[PDB]
Image 1: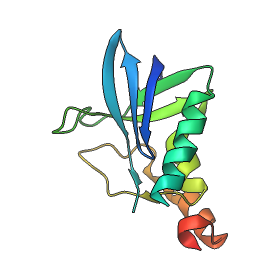
Image 2: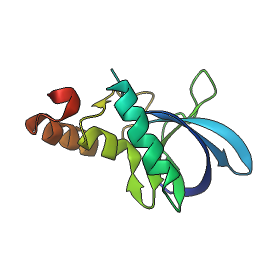
Image 3: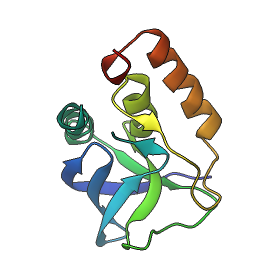
Amino acid sequence: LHKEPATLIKAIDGNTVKLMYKGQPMVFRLLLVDIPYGPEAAAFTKKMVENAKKIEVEFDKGQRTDKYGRGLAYIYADGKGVNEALVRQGLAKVAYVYKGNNTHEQHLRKAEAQAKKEKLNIWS
């Protein structure tokens, strides 16, 4: 896979963000991140993307938009994956794979196990 540049336009919620991507505005849904702490997840994502000096989007090898026209990607802020950071913090669960987008699934499951062991936030 590869990372592509994007500019934050607006934080929306724990697993949704609006970015300028290839000179066009687009709502992105964070791949493989489920949010049942909803306000907590929102604040966490908001801070991570607003404080970033560099935001990148990384599509996976499966379908790239959902039925609502949202881009389905891994989002990075200064190189750190937001999807994984939310799962590792116990602020989201790992979702079911959607349409072949599973590159980072195993890695996210490891983060989720560790958050669960630590009884963090949703795993309280």
